[PDB]
Image (cartoon, rainbow, N blue to C red; front, side, top):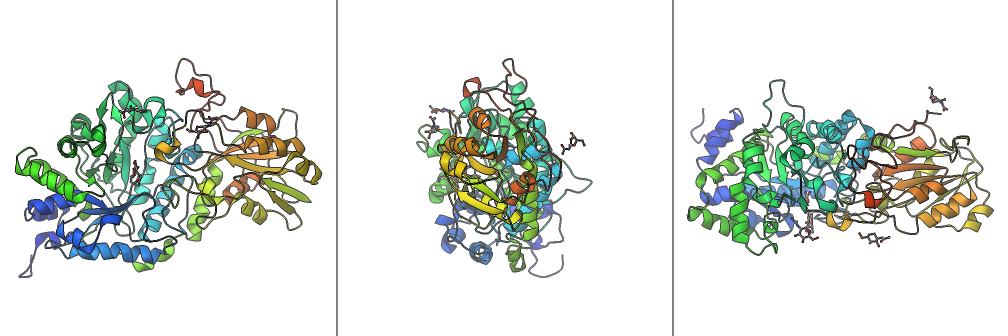
Length: 606
Ligand SMILES: CO[C@@H]1O[C@H](CO)[C@@H](O)[C@H](O)[C@H]1S[C@@H]1O[C@H](CO)[C@@H](O)[C@H](O)[C@H]1O
């Protein structure tokens, strides 16, 4: 079609399937296996990318060009890698992926949205869509084209360290919140076939429905463990949102570390090929989790040859290696060379990978747009996060007796007020895991507004605001305070580090609440990724708010505390009386909740 050196796969006017087939037909085995390989930026160099025909890069949690890097530093990094991949014989661009799971959260100055559990409290799928949209822009600001989100796990036991990454214990809520997908990717056409991948263009990103399947059903909430449930329960609780994702054109699906009735998901051909590909008709690419194939065996890594065979025969298309690429490539090449893995399986994985890259426009815009850099941390996005944070708050108590004047909303004018607690002025704690570092961190880790900062920005100029992190009872009684706001809760955690069998917040937390509330009427703001033992905090407090992990915009908290808006959030999870009850979900025999799923008190705006 019209020049003498014309190559159909390079012609942007041709249909994606024709471009895929035309490119696939020219590729060597090495070129094919290279597409199937995703590596960490930490092991990538121009020569490694070129010589191994690498298909994809990622940043794992905390893998950044440097601390504090600007949006343009990210763009330059990603373009440097792309430049190498475009210099190969076939010039196939790489796709760069990152965990942008509550904003573009690895990046300094990125807007940090509430974590998923809080978003489930909003019951507002359109808000989540808009959060998708903002997140796509902030990811493209850094030159990155692919976000490992949404997590559509249905957490069935809050002892799990990733329970905050699940919108709800109720699959219906999780289903509703798959609107993140068309936020990230754009809306699919009227005509769209369910299971086809979609991304609108250069201002959107490929999404990833993760982690397939039953990641939130593991025994005792143990991370990466076994999920014991008949096919009917799997299909009724853990699967449904995957079908909503297919309907909205999710481009990729990541496989779970977890097992189903003892079968490693990363080795499960019946579910990956038989169900996801052959029954749901998924036509995007299937990606492993980080060393997910390694973890097929025990010990992990003990038979990498079998890891590669089992995973690729099960139907995985791209492997998140992410470090030992030479070994992965060498072993997979051996398997194809000895007939253990047929060419048809390679060609299917590469078809899927190229389908997503061509569909999303990556061959037409392989490089970053520097005009997008300024999207990072844009005030419109912070305003959105602030709206989400406010809508996520669940008011659990507002008055010790039914006859008390309701404490909330608090007045903005008062002579003197106290702000206290370990979580009142700690941005890191209010963001939780997957913020700047993998495990999150403490203190002023990025740009945002702590609860203390938000109180000071909200109150009348005549209101004196005193901060004390852990005041004693006498300090409070002697202080002349009108009221206190006290914020406490969980420390940041991610993944197995957050698996917790007792779910009691660290001290001092409760002790500070008791000392503050003992002296002056108090509003307790509980920061957590999940329900935690709360009766003692409730007993001390006039009012108590479950604020979850609200992110960078602390003003979302004060917007509701001071009555600019009313509380509307409703628990997206059951709140247990005791961890001995667990697991306990809306539906079981012994359903005896402290607060039932859907509970939440309200207030009216002042
Ligand atoms: C970088 O993510 C985590 O890093 C630690 C330490 O290097 C690993 O040992 C963990 O098992 C992974 S977990 C895995 O990471 C994916 C990529 O960051 C992520 O998308 C997925 O949701 C996680 O399960």
